[PDB]
Length: 140
Length: 140
Ligand SMILES: CN(C(=O)N[C@@H]1COCC1(F)F)[C@@H](COc1ccccc1)c1cc[n+]([C@@H]2O[C@H](COP(=O)(O)OP(=O)(O)OC[C@@H]3O[C@@H](n4cnc5c(N)ncnc54)[C@H](O)[C@@H]3O)[C@@H](O)[C@H]2O)cc1
Ligand SMILES: CN(C(=O)N[C@@H]1COCC1(F)F)[C@@H](COc1ccccc1)c1cc[n+]([C@@H]2O[C@H](COP(=O)(O)OP(=O)(O)OC[C@H]3O[C@@H](n4cnc5c(N)ncnc54)[C@H](O)[C@@H]3O)[C@@H](O)[C@H]2O)cc1
Image (cartoon, rainbow over all chains, first blue to last red; front, side, top):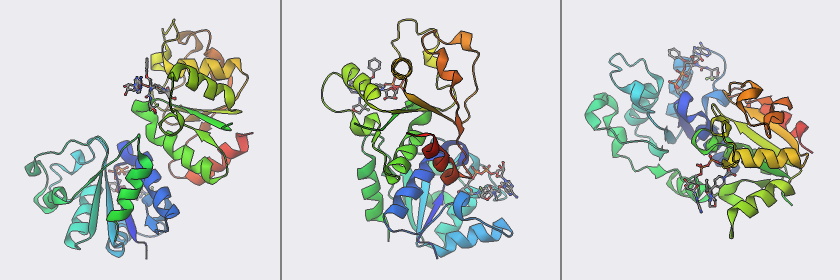
């Protein structure tokens, strides 16, 4: 029922993810971010259904955002889990690049390596309105 | 003419500072932040005029936000200059605390120790709108 899911890393991406939420809602999108819209019940189900329900998966690539996905053999890391769901479901994946270094794909789990083939949007501190505009152009 | 001046550290606080700006604009307040409002001319002049011009001074205390203030005995650091300006002008100072560890006064320059005597607001990741509502209570 939301159009946009926001996947982010708390310890480096929380503030950016929130700013993305606020801007997109301003522009008429219904947005899921965990802190606003993850409510009662077993969260493993709710989180994954929430990815499945949104056309758009916006992924915040703050510095090191994918480091916990590395060597996540049992799929216990939540950004890992969200990306796989977005990939499996063929979502409109929009990476947002905020000081991220592109790792060699093979440091990532096979089931999320394809995340790096989607075109991302550089988050510009100096030109935020234009960044926001570009993100809206990408959204389906 | 701006009602609110946002002073912040770029390396740790740029996202929060932009998040705060949007929320305050949505609530009808005119906000200076550099990356939107600092325009042509000598920036030393224009910034200081901007602090002097705004009833309210929102200071973003991201972690280590005052580190480059300490031992800054010549007032070269920009967060130091902004604070000193807001103090001298008797501005409504509003600290926003986001993982900031409170320092002993003695480690700060004498000219800006008084900033620690102001009542600050805890930035809550889980209750952002409540945080924003409290900030607006503080503002004049
Ligand atoms: C004039 N400057 C700009 O960045 N101008 C940009 C153009 O319009 C928008 C804009 F503001 F972003 C900078 C000036 O730097 C210094 C710093 C020391 C000595 C001389 C200049 C600016 C401005 C404002 N604040 C205030 O303080 C706080 C941030 O302080 P700090 O986190 O510690 O910031 P810093 O990272 O040490 O400064 C970074 C510098 O900022 C840029 N940059 C430096 N030179 C100039 C210059 N000539 N013209 C344009 N940009 C300049 C370069 O990126 C440098 O890296 C905030 O509250 C701000 O209000 C600090 C530095
Ligand atoms: C259900 N959890 C919540 O945080 N719930 C909060 C209450 O409602 C709103 C809310 F979401 F903020 C967490 C669950 O954590 C884990 C983590 C590992 C194993 C089991 C549970 C959640 C949820 C969503 N995301 C998604 O992923 C990304 C964030 O990933 P990371 O930065 O890496 O995340 P983390 O911060 O390391 O999470 C662990 C922390 O999460 C909290 N916390 C853990 N337990 C629960 C729990 N039972 N109920 C509430 N909070 C819980 C504690 O603060 C833990 O330290 C985003 O894209 C999110 O969509 C990750 C973790």
